[PDB]
Length: 361
Ligand SMILES: [Cl-]
Image (tube, rainbow, N blue to C red):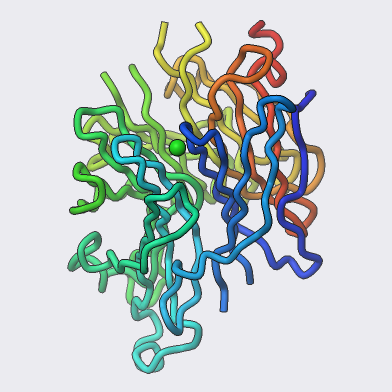
């Protein structure tokens, strides 16, 4: 398909950059591109949408120095823009850089921390890190071996409270001998991050997931990575606290046996339903290759997913999507950050709905 922009924003022959996260700032009309740099830290590149040239002008890479705990590796950048306050949240995971004394005695001891840094100046400067572990997870902490959030952008609902929903997953130590099994879930806050609730797990063996909100009443749809041949999806009518039965979305392939992370976002319908969904993920049946974009015009119905349009041929892995307002051709504008070329780079792609799905126009 034709695109407005395609450029590598992170590159490393040593596969130093992985796990992309993209965040669009609607007022500034800018993007924040985050990635993990292998202790492991989170880096960022700011990019302004230059209307006159309809191109994002990426600035110099910088380390998010605040997004780190002493003696810990930082990973899984999970950004969010709070439309009510304008504040930016960068949630992330912190794990000890070396085996701890506790782990020497208990191999599966949980030593993973949930953290956040916030910005009130559009991401130029960040607050000192805040450890949300105890407040968000509580007594369930010891029942897991580790957990993570995202990766990729989180969600803010259009409910009265403008609730924050952070997609996550935990490796549950259910069997003393058998390896911990991961299950996806959501963290939910109705007060802009002051308090948090941990939602119930969806089906077992679900990893990295992302959530979006759509009209159908408003529901939260969770799209997760699986070890099966298809993606796993579930919907919640209570902001992610409880999900209805998980479903296999056969139209969205997953390459076994490991699967791959994918991204999903909602955007205003270009036409009965209020929102449509756009999702990106590799399209090869058993390899992480051929990144494709899929559309769901009647979300989140599993059977409504479109055939994918190829965004990039070849090696492609993890990706993150963001809607960026209206494009130069009048149709919705999108930004996508994805891993490519055997993890040697993270590429930024910008395209419109009209470019990707011409049949719609
Ligand atoms: Cl903004």
